[PDB]
Figure 1: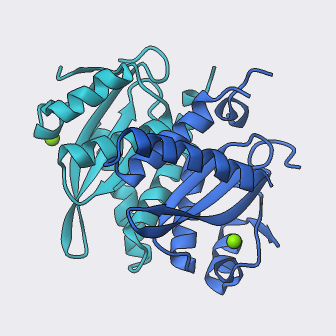
Figure 2: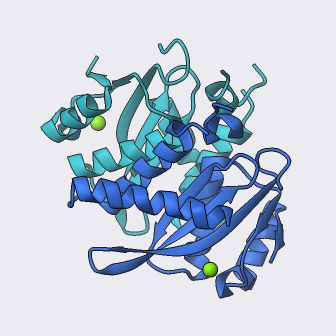
Length: 145
Length: 146
Ligand SMILES: [Mg+2]
Ligand SMILES: [Mg+2]
């Protein structure tokens, strides 16, 4: 749907169990390039949501238009304020399968080395999927930048 | 020093006071493009070192060569095993970058006292990599030129 990089992203929160806790992985995916940002948070309040959104912006750049579900955090005024501050249109699966690839990569890296910190695994997965996996022949990173 | 993006990085840890504590900002900067990665950690051990380096790789790409000081973390065996495992050359053969970031932090936290440190760090990165024009290019543009 996005016509170029950073036109439209889709975002969701998905869950992942690590050493007994069920973490919130805040996920952003660019609908043109497929490039992805994931941030491991403990919860899904507006603070964590904005926090993970800012991290995605450092990774991918600032999007024109983001699409989400009707989650409370996305509908909160804190988040609406952020969006307006940043000049981002906000409206209410590419995500489901992107999620799938990330989780299979965390499961693999954790099987190989059980004591791997969750952050390392997430950053290894992000680098693999964005920058290594070829799709035309291009990586998501190439098409993004 | 680096001849194209991701040829040679420099990294260092530097200190930043926020509220009570003295935080470790693990900084990696690409010597060709300028592009920067910064990870806020509570300490400067090999765990924290490796973690911050993986975040940088996810932000920046994998470098061929890294230059660091002689700090404990960098000389440890966990760090050396990470490097060889990733085909990164490491030597012990930045301070201006550290200064530009800390100045953006200070400015951000002066305008809004409650702004979380992590958000300030990510706002800085985005500004410094993708907004500041230098050449007439940003660091990001140079970093991603094929
Ligand atoms: Mg949801
Ligand atoms: Mg030092």
